[PDB]
Image (tube, coloured by chain):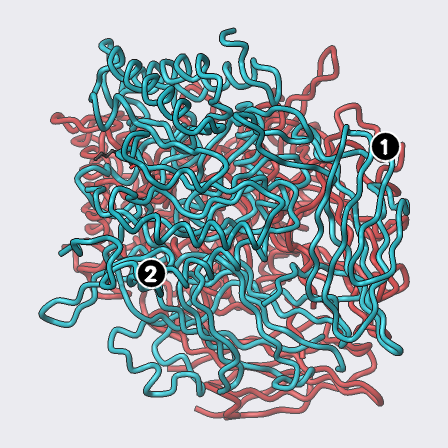
Chain colours: A cyan, B red
Amino acid sequence: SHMLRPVETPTREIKKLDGLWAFSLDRENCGIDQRWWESALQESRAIAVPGSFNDQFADADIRNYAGNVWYQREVFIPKAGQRIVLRFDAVTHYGKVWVNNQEVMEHQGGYTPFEADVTPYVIAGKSVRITVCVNNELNWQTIPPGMVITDENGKKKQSYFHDFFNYAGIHRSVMLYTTPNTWVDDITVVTHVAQDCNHASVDWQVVANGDVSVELRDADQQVVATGQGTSGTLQVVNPHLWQPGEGYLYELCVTAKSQTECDIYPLRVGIRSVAVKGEQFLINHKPFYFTGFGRHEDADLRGKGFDNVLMVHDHALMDWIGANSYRTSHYPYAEEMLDWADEHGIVVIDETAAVGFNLSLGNKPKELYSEEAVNGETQQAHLQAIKELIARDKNHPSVVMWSIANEPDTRPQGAREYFAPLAEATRKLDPTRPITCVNVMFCDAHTDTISDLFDVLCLNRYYGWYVQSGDLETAEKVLEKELLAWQEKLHQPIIITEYGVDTLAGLHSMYTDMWSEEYQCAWLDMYHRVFDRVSAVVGEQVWNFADFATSQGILRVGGNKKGIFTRDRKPKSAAFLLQKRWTGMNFGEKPQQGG
Amino acid sequence: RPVETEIKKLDGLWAFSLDRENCGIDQRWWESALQESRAIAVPGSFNDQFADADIRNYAGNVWYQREVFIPKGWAGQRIVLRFDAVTHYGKVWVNNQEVMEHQGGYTPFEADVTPYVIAGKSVRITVCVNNELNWQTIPPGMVITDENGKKKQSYFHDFFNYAGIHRSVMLYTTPNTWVDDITVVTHVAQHASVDWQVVANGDVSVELRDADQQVVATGQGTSGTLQVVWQPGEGYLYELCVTAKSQTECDIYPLRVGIRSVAVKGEQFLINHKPFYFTGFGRHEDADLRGKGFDNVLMVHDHALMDWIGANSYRTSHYPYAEEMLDWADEHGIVVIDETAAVGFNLSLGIGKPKELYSEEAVNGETQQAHLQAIKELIARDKNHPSVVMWSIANEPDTRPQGAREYFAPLAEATRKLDPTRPITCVNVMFCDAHTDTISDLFDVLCLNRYYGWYVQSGDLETAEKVLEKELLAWQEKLHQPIIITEYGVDTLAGLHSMYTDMWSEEYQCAWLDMYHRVFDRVSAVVGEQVWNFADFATSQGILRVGGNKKGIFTRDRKPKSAAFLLQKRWTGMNFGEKPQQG
Ligand SMILES: CCCCCCCCC[C@@H]1NC[C@@H](O)[C@H](O)[C@H]1C(=O)O
Ligand SMILES: CCCCCCCCC[C@@H]1NC[C@@H](O)[C@H](O)[C@H]1C(=O)O
């Protein structure tokens, strides 16, 4: 449907985000049968929302549990005559909500919010019970996809194809918000600029039988433009347009009035224009250079759960290190991260949860794009995730790119058949932004067959790590050669969205061999040397802020160790190399082929 | 503590600013939006939040600010602003009008803002937080200055001086007849529970249930309340609805209470007339990244670790914990020794200054008063909790200089008169043994901190066993009192191993915790053990702290050392609430 983030005005929120819900497992799938919605928690225990249920009890048998978990919470209802709505900003994978024995709504998104209108079903003044059924399972039509395997005892074991651990549960806000019966439930805003001198910001919104008078107030509450109608444009003059450095943000207050009731919604948008020209990524008609991380929503104890201290601290670290950009790696991030990126002018490459469409990253199906794995319904679900992501992050000026999928195996015939309609559909959904598909390493420029449909070429390369293990002299030649081959092929702006190596924070060696910090430094350094002599490399993005948790494997030593920082946010030796490089260059500009 | 039948203002981010030049109160920064502010998260200590070295140690004035919408549904009700905890000092302003202030730090403070607030429009909230300690703050300290005005704070406890807003901020609403004060005391012989009440223009009607609304008693009055006929295993707790009735509005307040009576008999600690044995940790309000800020995920996880390792009790070490810890504590029925921030009254703990600890320039007058205040507040907030079985006035004070007894006697007297239903204690330091301590008689349970084999007799088990044994049974023969060892632990690097089982290695933590447990087992007066710290925690910079205090069974990110499984074998291998029969 339509997605508007709620905000306090003559509108109200009761943060049911309160922790300490009742939590229980359903190892027998008796919950849907035995009507657990009715009343009690049976044999529950205290859990905390937001937060992943896997790491929260230090029980291994819970963290690998694959099935149905039950959340439970009684709450009181203060808003009368207002539309009361129950919003879940994120319930990872599947969630079915119940308000006092009655199914309200359900979702199969994972990292996208879903809400429901509960005005008839509640009465402001008495209690009410909310029971959530959260499913953490992945089959071939989920985004991301997976394979759940039962064995001889019927015990479910979830296997997937991405790297990060499949943290599940309620990860973001659960809120009970309250809006007048004539609401402003959808908005779209597109901005243009000409020579940083003047241009318009077209408006568009959806009401509940009310008219929309829209004003454009300033950063100090000064009206600069008005407008009367459901559509149309409106022009500023000599704007304070949104730059990657500062990030100026106008406050467009929209009004939807009825003959009796009225609703006012303030929506912050910044004037900026993002486009791709040849091999240049232009923000406000200036060629840009991306620097920063591909991070994860990962932490100790809470898993993929959200928390504010992590936001302010992580943004302080990136702010110190000189990073100006990041990419919401492998799933839509919490909207709060994108609000911060909006105010602080942080350019973001947004991505969907489509990751793992690849069976070469080592009882696996034998054809990746057959009916037994990634079929038409996988394509429908992928288009769904695109729809929801764009419908949530469409107005945020910090998003400059949509990324449909991550590292798909494109060698087999049919990858183009699967991905081309999704490129067409995404271009038809949001024309204001470039589109991309992050490229796997074993699909170099001479075997890929998908990168033509996208505006920006994103690359994940690990020459010298997975291949040429320990060889810098050779990985330099290979890396430079394939980079110039991508240039000779597509003449596109090339952002390296992943490049990193594993490093035991504390492992040193005089020989600068793999897994030591000296190898991380020398490796990133050589990669930077190659980066500086390719004209079409419009951005670099290291593989990963900090070490994150992965599934158990013989390649993951307590998870992925390719982070610049540790899981507790401590810098390895390479963090200060990146400090020197990024903070030493001119902001938003590519190095002049050398310092 | 609020319930209803509110809008939690601690949601999201606040504007944060520093006052290095100390211009805030003079230039009236609360009457405007903070110039040059940055986003900060509440709850959470401001020191660790920005990875800034200069912000972490800053000693002065910090400014929080946040606009909020007051809901329309609270038209004619009193609107109250509650700060569950603002560490050390806080002065709160509501939209150009000064409302409140408090020098507590680890206890809440609330203020009535009904006139200054018009429910429906947005108002701004500005908080001035101070993190300074002199000799009259609890805990005490002293600040020093030089040229360029750089302020540098020095204190006498171990843990790092985290500050800021550490617990939720509430904005609750009650009808014009509210239940401001409640008290409940439970008895049990081989019983019932007197009730209390304070209100304004309202009568008191008290009823109480069990599982769900199943009343099993009642009462109409501010006394008596006795009727029909809470354990450390599960923790059965009844629900006591209090009603305050007026001509127009009515108030209902639910208070969970568990039937229990704690008392000391000879050298036994009796909870419900049964001898007990304390096992568990002396923990801290410390975490990665957020300082002393509260968080539910951490409480759930740490309670999972304590449940797994077999702990049955712990002590809110060196300051009042967040009350959520105590609600959980009486829910799952874990025994809690509650303690004030009174720590650091000692000049002998020197890493290797006034001249006498109980002089006028240090610890005299307002110091004793404000200590009695920290008592009064801790008790006024945690009195009704059945999980609290003990009072702890102070921790590790130097009682050797002249005038210590003259200081500690009145505090014991007043505290005993305030809450006579629970035993009282004072954790004494190691440098004051049985032949030199002069205060352990004023208290019901004697608490001991002992580090034989670490600070003295460093690395020698064969003699530290003898010294610990002699000191222990000499205490027993001296005062014939119940002795809980509230601190015993040694530092340990998480990954350091050593074949020789020498200091700082995990083998030394294992073998050192073991000998202490045998000497514990051959002493009849030891009514419990609490390994020093649950998890490694942050302290001030010293040559004895290797990135904080490493005396934890778990690391800071909650990962177990070799001793965690030893203690999980010891505490769950014995019977719950029972001490081994000398083996
Ligand atoms: C057959 C040739 C294979 C080439 C190597 C492919 C490496 C893919 C790297 C992986 N790319 C995806 C990312 O989520 C992971 O964290 C990253 C990694 O594992 O470090
Ligand atoms: C004879 C006495 C020699 C010196 C003993 C010093 C004992 C001080 C105990 C200290 N008591 C306070 C506690 O927070 C600290 O963690 C603990 C410590 O040492 O780390």
Tag 1 residue: A238
Query: Is B532 on the left-hand or right-hand side of B207?
Result: left
Q: Is residue B500 above or below residue B206?
A: above
Q: Position of residue B238 (x, y in %)?
A: 49, 81
Quadrant of the frame with the N terminus of chain B: bottom right
Judge: label 1 CB < 8 Å from ligand 1.
Answer: no
Q: Position of residue A567 (x, y in %)?
A: 39, 37
Q: Position of residue B482 (x, y in %)?
A: 36, 56
Query: A412 and A337: which one is in front?
Result: A412
**Could you say which quadrant of the image residue A152 lies in?**
bottom left
Q: Residue at x 73, y 71 (%)?
A: A179
Q: Residue furthest top?
A: A595
Q: Is residue A93 above or below residue B196?
A: above
Name the chain under label 2: B
Q: Which mark is residue B312?
A: 2
Task: Using the numbered discs, state the Cα–Cα distance from disc 1 to disc 2 in whole angstroms.
Answer: 68 Å
Name the chain under label 1: A
Q: Is residue B398 above or below residue A414?
A: above
Query: A87 and B549: which one is in front?
Result: A87
Q: Residue at x 72, y 43 (%)?
A: A191
Q: Residue at x 31, y 36 (%)?
A: A448
Residue B155 in sight: no
Q: Position of residue B135 (x, y in %)?
A: 67, 33
Amino acid tagged 1: Asn
Say what secondary structure mark 2 lies in. Answer: loop
Which marked residue is nearer to the observer: mark 1 or mark 2?
1
Crowding at dot 2, Cα within 10 Å, few <14 / some 14-19 / many 20+, comes out as many
